[PDB]
């Protein structure tokens, strides 16, 4: 973890125009490889920071990433009219060269719809997106282009979200840190991020909600389940290190999250099921209940 992930930050006077090209390319499923991060960042820069590079670079998003394995490199690029001109191989330039209804905010809010069920699989995730689109449409909150509501387009964005850390991180951060009087796209993003809390971490949510009482639920005090309580406590201690991102650890593939796999805790899960029918703070609460047992 000594070596950093380096992300070029392309500074253009063209940003809205370049974002339209970026959106067009992602829709066509262009495989940007190592450059995808840089182009997704530019969308976030335009939408969340009103194109203000200085404020983006001193933002809490960037401060966190710089402290956790990333380095950002500003490259000033005057006179760019085509994405090809920002590419730092062979076939991507051809694809972009062949390039002949929305905006960056819309692209990002649509992408955020994939967060709540991303880790559950394509079928479940796409069904969730379709239902959410109809909810937002009925509340009059947002409407997406005709082209984006095909199963085919959703499969493209699903794969983009599944594989790209930075866009998930920036959406999640945005969802927790909006500027006053936020717009419809930000409302959708913040809603998506709220829905995504503890996605892929069912055992954490349910243990903290149903087994925590503070003491452990009486069924979680037996010596038979003591191995599971100890294992959970250790795993939760490590999760708490991720601070406000802990509920999203499975979404963001953060360290130590494999230790919280559901299957690793059958006895606690069974207890939680019987009952039902920040993270740093709750770890301290769990520490307290455990010690008492």
Image (spheres, helix red, strand yellow):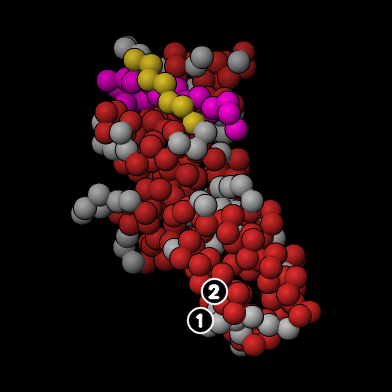
Residue at the image position 37 percent from the left and 25 percent from the top: 18
In this rendering, the count of numbered labels is 2
Using the image, determine if residue 46 lies above or below residue 280: above
| Mark 2 or mark 1, earlier in chain | 1
Instruction: Determine the residue located farthest toward the left in the rendered image.
Output: 181
Disc 1 is placed on an element classified as: loop
| Residue name at image x 51 percent, y 72 percent | 285
Q: Residue 123: in sight, yes or no?
A: no
- Kind of element beneath mark 2: helix
For the record, the magenta segment spans: 1-18
Give residue 97's position: percent from left, percent from top. Answer: 51, 16
Q: Which residue is mark 1?
A: 214
Q: Name the residue rendered at 76%, 80% in the picture.
A: 223
Residue 101: in magenta span: no
Task: Point out which mark residue 23 bears.
Answer: none
Callout 1 environment at 10 Å: few (<14), some (14 to 19), or many (20+)? few
The single residue placed furthest to the front in the displayed view is 291
Q: Position of residue 226 (x, y in %)?
A: 73, 75
Which residue in the protein does label 2 denote? 288
- Please give the name of the residue rendered at 64% of the width and 88% of the height, measured from the top-left corner: 218
CB under 8 Å between discs 2 and 1: yes
Residue 6 included in the magenta stretch of the image = yes
Q: Nearer the viewer, residue 253 or 157?
A: 253
- Which of the 4 image quadrants contains residue 133? bottom left
Q: Position of residue 158 (x, y in %)?
A: 58, 47
């Amino acid at each position: 973890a000594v070596r950093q992930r380096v992300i070029p930050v392309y500074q253009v006077n063209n940003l809205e125009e370049i974002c339209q090209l970026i959106i067009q390319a992602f829709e066509a499923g262009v495989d940007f490889q190592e450059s995808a991060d840089s182009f997704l960042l530019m969308l976030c820069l335009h939408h969340a920071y009103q194109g203000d590079y200085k404020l983006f670079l001193e933002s809490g998003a960037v401060k966190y990433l710089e402290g956790h394995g990333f380095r950002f490199e500003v490259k000033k690029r005057d006179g760019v009219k085509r994405l090809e001109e920002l590419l730092p191989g062979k076939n991507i330039k051809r694809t972009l060269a062949a390039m002949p209804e929305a905006n960056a905010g819309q692209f990002l809010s649509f992408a955020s719809l994939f967060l709540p069920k991303l880790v559950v699989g394509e079928k479940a995730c796409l069904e969730k997106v379709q239902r959410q689109i109809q909810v937002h449409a009925e509340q009059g909150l947002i409407q997406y282009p005709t082209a984006w509501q095909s199963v085919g387009h959703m499969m493209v964005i699903f794969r983009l979200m599944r594989t790209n850390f930075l866009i998930k991180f920036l959406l999640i951060h945005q969802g927790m840190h909006m500027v006053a009087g936020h717009d419809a796209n930000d409302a959708v993003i913040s809603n998506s991020v709220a829905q995504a809390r503890f996605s892929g971490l069912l055992i954490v949510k349910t243990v903290l909600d149903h087994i925590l009482q503070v003491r452990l639920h009486p069924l979680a005090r037996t010596a038979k389940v003591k191995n599971e309580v100890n294992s959970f406590k250790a795993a939760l201690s490590s999760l708490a290190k991720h601070g406000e991102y802990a509920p999203f650890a499975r979404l963001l593939n953060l360290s130590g999250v494999n230790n919280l796999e559901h299957g690793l805790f059958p006895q606690l899960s069974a207890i939680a099921l019987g009952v039902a029918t920040n993270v740093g703070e709750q770890y301290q609460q769990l520490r307290e209940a455990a010690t008492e047992a």
